[PDB]
Image (cartoon, rainbow, N blue to C red; front, side, top):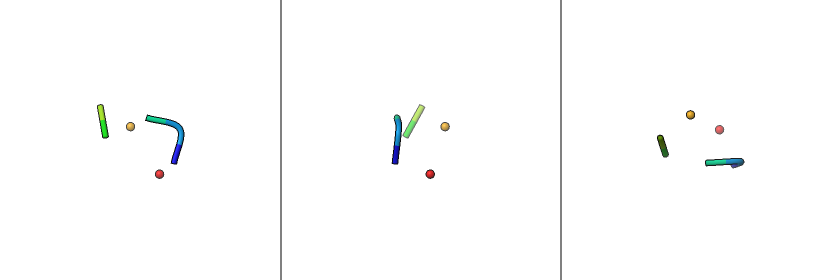
Length: 7
């Protein structure tokens, strides 16, 4: 959820 480069 933070950022899909990575929840």
